[PDB]
Image (cartoon, rainbow over all chains, first blue to last red; front, side, top):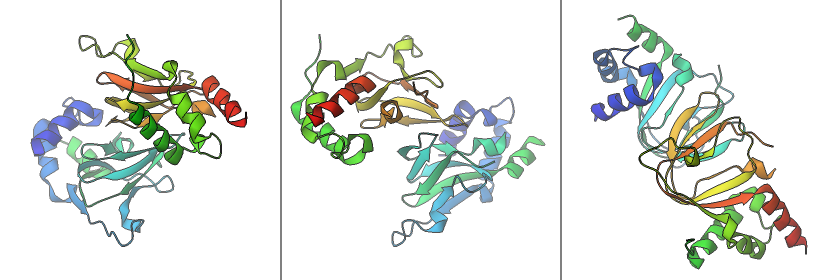
Length: 125
Length: 137
């Protein structure tokens, strides 16, 4: 549940290292409601605007971790394409600009979304 | 010791590449020539995963900024990829592929490391270009 996510972030994602963030602070953040977001997939318009979490032509505002669902990611100068799912994450740059990738929903998504402001606020702790 | 890959798996691999990867399009390489290439012993490779040394050098298929000149498709197994300017990390499995640009040294902006024993298709630039000439003759 939230334990898998906080464990994963603290272990794999530097900006959420326990050196920088109190585990209590991290979980309290995962709980705060604006961080738990959903993306409803309109299978009628697969390329609908709201399906795009990241675009190379749009500034990175937030870090995202996929809890549930699938996204298509084209990333890097080679623009390698992948189908990514739960516990893939994006926008660490937001918490440490436009990304070198595009990320599009392929299904309903449950997401953790953390803006630079929420992160910096959580550091003031 | 070198295991014979199932002929139907190599056929599935050929159909997949011909459909999904532009450098292997039938407009560039005939499906027959591609299948023949995928059957060559040097193209069928493995990574023996050393669980007592998970960062062993032979576990790395690609390394950021290190010149490379081969394409890889994973037939079986799991890899971790760290990619892009942010070095985002995620795990990939069977029938993911890498190094297309190495077939037009290219230096990738990703690192790819085995997380398990791997069974691989490995195509070098010279093997690819030789195959393009074979499609012509």
